[PDB]
Image (cartoon, coloured by chain):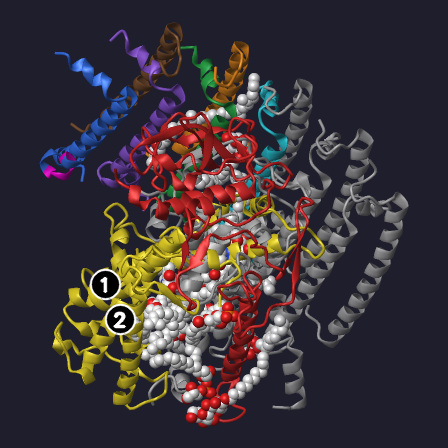
Chain colours: E orange, F brown, G red, H green, I purple, K cyan, M blue, N yellow
Amino acid sequence: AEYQNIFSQVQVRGPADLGMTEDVNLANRSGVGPFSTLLGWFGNAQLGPIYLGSLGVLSLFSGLMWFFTIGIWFWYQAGWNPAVFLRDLFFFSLEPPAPEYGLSFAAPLKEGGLWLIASFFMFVAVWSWWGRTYLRAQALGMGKHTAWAFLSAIWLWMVLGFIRPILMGSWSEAVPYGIFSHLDWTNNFSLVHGNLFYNPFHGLSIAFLYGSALLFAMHGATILAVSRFGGERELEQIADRGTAAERAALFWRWTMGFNATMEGIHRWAIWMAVLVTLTGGIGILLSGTVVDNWYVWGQNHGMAPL
Amino acid sequence: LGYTGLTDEQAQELHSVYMSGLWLFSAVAIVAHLAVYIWRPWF
Amino acid sequence: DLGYTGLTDEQAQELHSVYMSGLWLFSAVAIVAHLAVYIWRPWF
Amino acid sequence: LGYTGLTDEQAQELHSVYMSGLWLFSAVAIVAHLAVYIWRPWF
Amino acid sequence: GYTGLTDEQAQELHSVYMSGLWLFSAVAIVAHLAVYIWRPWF
Amino acid sequence: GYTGLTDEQAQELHSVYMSGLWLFSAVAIVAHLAVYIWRPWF
Amino acid sequence: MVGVTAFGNFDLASLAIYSFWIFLAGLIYYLQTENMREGYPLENEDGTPAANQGPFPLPKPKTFILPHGRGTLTVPGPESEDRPIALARTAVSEGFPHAPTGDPMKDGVGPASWVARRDLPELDGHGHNKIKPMKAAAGFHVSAGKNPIGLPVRGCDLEIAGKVVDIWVDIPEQMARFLEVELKDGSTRLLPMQMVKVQSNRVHVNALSSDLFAGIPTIKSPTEVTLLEEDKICGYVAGGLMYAAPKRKS
Amino acid sequence: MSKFYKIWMIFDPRRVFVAQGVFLFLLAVMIHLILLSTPSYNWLEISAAKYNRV
Amino acid sequence: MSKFYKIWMIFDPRRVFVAQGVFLFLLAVMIHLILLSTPSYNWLEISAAKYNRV
Amino acid sequence: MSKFYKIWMIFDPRRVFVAQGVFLFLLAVMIHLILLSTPSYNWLEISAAKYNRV
Amino acid sequence: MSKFYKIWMIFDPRRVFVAQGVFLFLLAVMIHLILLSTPSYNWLEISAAKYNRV
Amino acid sequence: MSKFYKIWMIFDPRRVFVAQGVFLFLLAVMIHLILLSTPSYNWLEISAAKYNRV
Amino acid sequence: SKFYKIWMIFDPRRVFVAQGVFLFLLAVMIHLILLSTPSYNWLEISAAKYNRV
Amino acid sequence: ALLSFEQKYRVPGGTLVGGNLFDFWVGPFYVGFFGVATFFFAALGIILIAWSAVLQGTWNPQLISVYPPALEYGLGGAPLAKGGLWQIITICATGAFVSWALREVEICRKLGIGYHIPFAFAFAILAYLTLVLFRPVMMGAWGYAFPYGIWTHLDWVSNTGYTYGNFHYNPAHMIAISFFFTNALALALHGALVLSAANPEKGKEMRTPDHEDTFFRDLVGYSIGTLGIHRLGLLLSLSAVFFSALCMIITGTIWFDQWVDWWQWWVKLPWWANIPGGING
Ligand code: BCL
Ligand code: BCL
Ligand SMILES: CC[C@H]1c2cc3[nH]c4c(c3C)C(=O)[C@H](C(=O)OC)c4c3nc(cc4[nH]c(cc(n2)[C@@H]1C)c(C(C)=O)c4C)[C@@H](C)[C@@H]3CCC(=O)OC/C=C(\C)CCC[C@H](C)CCC[C@H](C)CCCC(C)C
Ligand SMILES: CC[C@H]1c2cc3[nH]c4c(c3C)C(=O)[C@H](C(=O)OC)c4c3nc(cc4[nH]c(cc(n2)[C@@H]1C)c(C(C)=O)c4C)[C@@H](C)[C@@H]3CCC(=O)OC/C=C(\C)CCC[C@H](C)CCC[C@H](C)CCCC(C)C
Ligand SMILES: CC(C)=CCC/C(C)=C/C=C/C(C)=C/C=C/C(C)=C/C=C/C=C(C)/C=C/C=C(\C)CC/C=C(\C)CCC=C(C)C
Ligand SMILES: CC(C)=CCC/C(C)=C/C=C/C(C)=C/C=C/C(C)=C/C=C\C=C(C)\C=C\C=C(/C)CC/C=C(\C)CCC=C(C)C
Ligand SMILES: CCCCCCCCCCCCO[C@@H]1O[C@H](CO)[C@@H](O[C@H]2O[C@H](CO)[C@@H](O)[C@H](O)[C@H]2O)[C@H](O)[C@H]1O
Ligand SMILES: [Fe+3]
């Protein structure tokens, strides 16, 4: 039929690109991995090379120890039985200390201590990775948009695991490390605080997640629609506007009365995406500390019938 | 062999300094462990 | 070469001298603080 | 077999030092296991 | 072949690999004998 | 016609493969005889 | 802090939501002004500035330094659309279509439009040409899918217009950009990969009929394509979808 | 029979050795954990019962 | 019967050997697990009942 | 040793100083937070109990 | 056995040492944690009960 | 034994020192946290019970 | 005869791979179905015959 | 109005219906057959929502709710005060959405670009029709659809979810949530990477796609590419909406119980069904 430019028709392979040098320590950059045809049908086939520095080593060891702690707790919870491990893999959980321990570090290993150890490992891993995202952009002379967009997700992560439990006075307020157990935690969080639907910042977070899906479906469809004019080369369209950028702007201007630029659409994108967790962290931080019943709060604020 | 480009003398000097650091760390750790065992033996 | 960072032996030795002065200052203040806390409320 | 640009004599030297480290580690582990077994046998 | 190894290279590599395999199997045999004497599974 | 192996190379490779298959089958037959003497399934 | 209000029902949650409303108003203002760096100020259908410029002022100009000694771009700035446009207005009133006064594909108007981009090749990060013929590209080869080289090319009139002789690959991204097609007269044209359908025994180009392949704009250098030439070629081929409609399914 | 030395002509020693090490370690770990989960072969619990350690 | 070697002229040795090794391991694991599941052939429980280890 | 000063000939001073600043800040915050979370070492609660302020 | 050294002509010493160190540390931590979870081999609880501490 | 220094032949000093510091710091924090988890070795609780504090 | 013309339409590699997969799946299916019925479950028949359970 | 480059693009043609009858622009907007249809449907829907607010007795925008017919009406018409207004507004909304998609198709044809945007909008329209048309018709009542209120459609979401216990345990719901989360993450990363390339450290030259590829290869070891990221975004969004529509179309039609009980099939597999230990032993 008509080629919609979703999967490549022809794959071409050349020498692997080793990347730009700039101010990057090339000794900390590994070699190029293999080429993936399966990945090349959709995007780039080349795997690697990766950069491994001091913060990279710290982040990998910390995250590996986090995964190892959770996994060995799961193996203990299975009785060291591999069949039980596979049967109950989604039912295992590393739970925070019980509420009677407050914020103290005196909880036993099977009753909260191991969760604290794993949480320290995760803390170090995630903050090391944030520093890594900053420094990798600094080495190439790029702006630090990735680092400050990652900080928006780190904000919600900190509120869920660190800030709100401290403000609430117990580690039991934090999220367990498990597949079904963190879903149970989410449901019980909504149930305990009234209805999280009636949290205005939960609503804002949902609006911005829906808008992220909206905007990035729109952007992907727009770029694929003008890719016949080389619209996927967005940096060159910013530097030297072509007919792809003009047609993309005019479609949306004729459709909804206003458009963007080849640059400013990505400002819309970054802000719509970061506002999800930006509003989510505020919504979680206000639960239990300021509002204990969100439905009654919405009733008192004109959102629900009295 | 050699990958980082260090001569024999350079490697020997670096190893000497690293070994000094390791011995100071281990001496402090041994003193701390002896103090804890006197305070509360774990055997 | 004599190093990776690009510091002369004398530059490195001077910087280490200043660093150890700062470290000894911090450690002296910490030792006094620990002594005061232990006298106020010992943990052993 | 030249997979890593490493000569035969360099391989011999590196293996000698690696095995020296391996035997130190193994001797320490044997002594530790002996002490644990005398303290609390697991058989 | 595909690896480009010479015939004598294959001889030496297989000799060393087989020596390691025999050492591993001898240790495994001793371990299995000790376990069977301690607590047989048949 | 795809691997490019010659007649002699293919014959040598199949001879070694057959030697391995017979060794594996002999070990499996001995193990099966041991199990049958232990607990026959017929 | 539960239930503590400064006045009325105003607690920290109300303060946070009103603060976010103020912040969102400011952010949306900033985002809309950031997107007025191209195409503004607005103008009438005769090119003169429009009385209505909207509610958002133009942002203060910003400057890009171009990577390879290619100069400096200031936006928003003076506009560059000075090439003649072969369109005549079909109505005195504003807001009605302008009809072509000739062949729209040759004049580059409508869906066949092109922009006066720089008459220089796009460079990768190392200063070399970004798009190169596969045979000119060192070490490049087809790794998966059907190789289109050698296949005949069929137009939308179900007629053969040439044969594929090369693939123009994008060296950094390692993707095929253009197919080089040799025509009857022995000359060659570039066709974007996004506008062709590679089949088992042919390459089908639904946009152009067999007689419109010779009208594709030609590139100056046989081993080099510029942004201007790329833009002209892509505009011609895509305008074929609308201006070659009377020659479909034959 | 004694011509197995040609196996390295076809297979890269690096990949073969890495895969064999990973497979052997995983198999050994699985067997050890199966024995540990088995109450009749849990050697720590057997010793605890033998020496009255609980 | 005396011409099976020509399989190697059609099938690459690396892929054939990898596929056969994986198939052999999976078949052996399946048969061992099937025997383990049946109480009359589970050798661990058989020995546990024989020697009164529980 | 009397030759630690060459650690500065290996490592960039800026990175070392930033790493120490971050590590010391986080270590101090962590220890102070643990002490506050311990009821027997929360100095505000100790003073409230001692001076009868609640 | 007197010829294992040429393994260093196949494998990169740096990769081997990094992977070996990570594997050995994880195995040691696993064994220590398994021993801790075992009531008869948790040396901390053994000493707590021995010296009448908790 | 008396030949170890040649680690510095094949391993970059900066990478080794960074990895060693990361490992030592993580291990020390883990051991201290495990000790705080055990009631018989939580020194803060031990001193609280010894001096009759909250 | 003349069945050899089948090696004029299909690739022999694909033919052999598909036929091997087919035969293995069929054999596994039949063995499992036999194990499903207690009449031809040789492990269970052996257990009943020798009073192993 | 006009953008500085707009004039050469405003040409006749590209209309599916109407020819030159509606081929013009109102301000920046393009009007067509489907533009006129969209305006009529949207205006009627909004005015009827205001009239429903008049009937309901509130003018608070956050308290206005248009409720579907009761379950007693089945799939038949309902009085306008009870559920008839909801049915008319739903018809108006469907007309407005489909006419919006077809107007986008016309604009795509006029501009000579691909039809990816109307196709991606059809996915959202299909999810909406699943929630208001397909699932209620399968279930047998218009009252299983959601009301048109800012906070009462959240009440519908909560009630429908808790009919089946915790709705987190719907597996297609899990897949759709994974797709939504991955899409938001990818949108953040893509916006950040393009902005960081176009806006370097001050005084520096613009960065190239080579720097973007280098930065994510340094970070995660893989870069999907400039085309790959936009394809990935389209597919992530469309997959999230597809799996949402699927999880809602299976709910209450082939699954009627608590979704947490569905996962017992994996736990109760014959080989590990009865092994003691763990969570389920
Ligand atoms: C998706 C499955 C659920 C659903 C569950 C949720 C949950 C859970 C939440 C919402 C929230 C919203 N939903 Mg809802 N929502 C559903 C279906 C809809 C429909 C529809 C026609 O299908 C629409 C119009 C909306 C609209 C709304 C907005 C009130 C709000 C923000 C969403 C958003 O910004 O997305 C992204 C789109 C954009 C960013 C573009 C702008 C969207 C504008 C703001 C739409 C406004 C609609 C307007 C109030 C009414 C339209 C007609 C009027 C007469 C003009 N919902 C169904 C039944 N929805 C959130 C909220 O805060 O409500 C109080 C919230 O927490
Ligand atoms: C009964 C269930 C509850 C409910 C209770 C919760 C709770 C509790 C929360 C939400 C929150 C959210 N809810 Mg809700 N939610 C409900 C119903 C809904 C409905 C609906 C249609 O019904 C919608 C669409 C949503 C949607 C959402 C999102 C808008 C928001 C999650 C943002 C996010 O992306 O976090 C995902 C991103 C993160 C968690 C941050 C991740 C960043 C870190 C650093 C990741 C590190 C990775 C780690 C190192 C692992 C590495 C692994 C390797 C790399 C492989 N809710 C109801 C009423 N919901 C959250 C929120 O913030 O809103 C206030 C939240 O806390
Ligand atoms: C704006 C808000 C959204 C957002 C944004 C966002 N996330 C981000 C970023 C941004 C902007 C990054 O820059 C950062 C990133 O790196 O992206 C690729 C990241 C990131 N977001 C991630 C996850 C994530 N984001 C989520 C959500 C969101 N992220 C929001 C929707 C979620 C959800 C919804 O739950 C998740 C799970 C990561 C992919 C990444 C941060 C990764 C990180 O910190 O990793 C630390 C590592 C660990 C803790 C685990 C390591 C486990 C390994 C097993 C370690 C051992 C490896 C081993 C040694 C390998 C050995 C190999 C050899 C043997 C061969
Ligand atoms: C399928 C992938 C995602 C997606 C894609 C998508 N959406 C799109 C498009 C695409 C590709 C467009 O091209 C189109 C557009 O032009 O966007 C600017 C659009 C669009 N998606 C929109 C919204 C939207 N998309 C959503 C979701 C999604 N859109 C998906 C997650 C949501 C959610 C989740 O709530 C909303 C609210 C619009 C901004 C726009 C379509 C505008 C339109 O239809 O215009 C004509 C109709 C009107 C002007 C309004 C008619 C009003 C009715 C007559 C009465 C009210 C009815 C309504 C049901 C009441 C609701 C009450 C309560 C539930 C609040
Ligand atoms: C280049 C030159 C000259 C030299 C290079 C130097 C070199 C090469 C050095 C390397 C020397 C060394 C250490 C070599 C070591 C080799 C080793 C340990 C080999 C070991 C082999 C072991 C093998 C097969 C074991 C196979 C076992 C199998 C299937 C078991 C299958 C079990 C099943 C199916 C489980 C059944 C039971 C249950 C499910 C409960
Ligand atoms: C086979 C082998 C060997 C291994 C298998 C390994 C396996 C199976 C692993 C399974 C891993 C799984 C399921 C993980 C699931 C995780 C999930 C859902 C997590 C969800 C949310 C988590 C959050 C918000 C955590 C936030 C934590 C934060 C902010 C910070 C905390 C910091 C603290 C508390 C430090 C405390 C300590 C000190 C101060 C010293
Ligand atoms: C970045 C900026 C940071 C600073 C931000 C400061 C924002 C300040 C915004 C103040 C707006 C106050 O807005 C007003 O608050 C009062 C507080 O009771 C609300 O509350 C009022 O109405 C409701 C509804 O009838 C009554 O139940 C309530 O008793 C009455 O007080 C009003 O409905 C609201 O209109
Ligand atoms: Fe983009």
Mark before the other along the chain sequence, 1 or 2:
2
Marks 1,2: beta carbons within 8 A: yes
Q: Which mark is residue N251?
A: 1
Q: Crowding at label 1, few (<14), some or many (≥20) Cα neighbours within 10 Å?
A: many
Above-or-below relation of G211 to N107: above
Question: Can residue A224 be spotted in the picture?
Answer: yes
**Circle 1 marks a residue in which chain?**
N
How far across and down, in percent of the image, does residue G94 sit?
43, 68
Q: Residue at x 52, y 47 (%)?
A: A233
Q: Residue at x 35, y 22 (%)?
A: I16
Above-or-below relation of A136 to A145: above
Above-or-below relation of N152 to H37: below
Q: Crowding at label 2, few (<14), some or many (≥20) Cα neighbours within 10 Å?
A: some
Instruction: Give the residue number, with chain letter if any, for mark 2.
Output: N160
Q: Is residue F13 left or right of residue I42?
A: right
Instruction: Considering the whole magenta stretch, tell me its main secondary structure.
Output: helix
Please state which of residues A202 and N134 is positioned toward the viewer in this rendering: N134
Looking at the rendering, the stretch of residues picked out in magenta corresponds to M34-38
**Three-letter residue code for mark 1:** Thr
Q: Which mark is residue N46?
A: none
